[PDB]
Image (cartoon, rainbow, N blue to C red; front, side, top):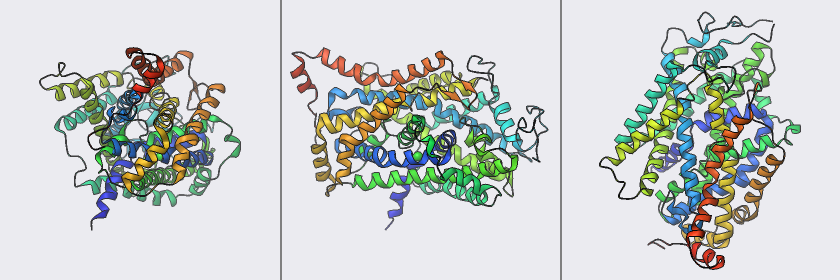
Length: 534
Ligand SMILES: [Cl-]
């Protein structure tokens, strides 16, 4: 009967800010068309196989967080790594909401703030209507993004003064997150439909408008037709692989929990394929929506598409709000779009904080148990994350955000986590045995492509990307202007290492704390710990 409900659950987990904001920004940063080829290749070879692996593993083990790795306890540190990654997400992901929140609070006006060059934050280069020195001029959307919301400083060396307008919005977002996490709201219980169809509808509307703009065809062509000389650069491969591993929540421990929630005999293969296709399609649709507006902007200003908008994380706050200035009733559509953005970000933040706090409290001993341990733990986590984000709501804040975006919960971190997960499942545990278990779970034997991806294809893809980036290293640059100094990249590597060291350190600690020679230690510490069902 109501099979559609299940579908909504899928989209209720699939669409997020990694599709509407990160995918377009990454695509524009690496060039439109050339980014899709590694995207498709990694989605087929690394994305979907790891998606199915994680979902099936969670379903088979019937447990999420760190316990899922009881198939190979020696590598349980993998779970710890995930618990770190999600934490870092909760640190900087909320930042997007704050900026979005700001826009929403500025949306309810008679005329939109980012449509006039007669404000105080604007520069003398602000020109409302473009005509035929001609490069220094900046559109009012860019002025609002880089003069009021961000107040961008010279570089990461100059943090500057705290931005109170965005600080209060960030505090409001964190208080709302705490209130809903403490209440344990049944978000997307039955009204899932709206929370699962409000984005697409709005996006569909945007797409229609995005198509009816002169010069949008050039933007779409730039989005689709690739430049083949950019395939040799390993940066596009990092961006595509990590974007897939980010939008799919691969390595963050989300797919494992989702699998653990399902029934034992549920068709996890179909669920994984459907979820991956939904997520990729949403990313592609957001790509159309952004790039049509980008082509319109490039035609209007007369500059190239690659230089019209910011290659920094502000595309969702430059490409999307600009589109709103074209709709018949701009403030209404601004409020609607940023309300949808806020709802998506809040759902993702709620589930992330729920999972992180639940796992952290699980690992804590019974002696540490406070009276209101849930309330106090959520409050402490939110306060600590707000204190950390105080570094992102300063003038030199976006730079820090970039450091949290490229290096933390992305980049080589996700490659490391995915590679180790594939090695543990396929090699140490046994890919053949896991395939047999999935066959006995869901009935039919999956395609052998899954086994070949777990065993040799995906681990070698991750290792090859990692090696081609370590050998050919390019310092992180923000929006083609700010080349990061040595200490900024050192801090980024500090985040990456704080995430990636969980696996080797856990393995060494487990081996050292065991007894006997290394052979029997390895044999005993990798023995799976089966649950009651198995
Ligand atoms: Cl995606």
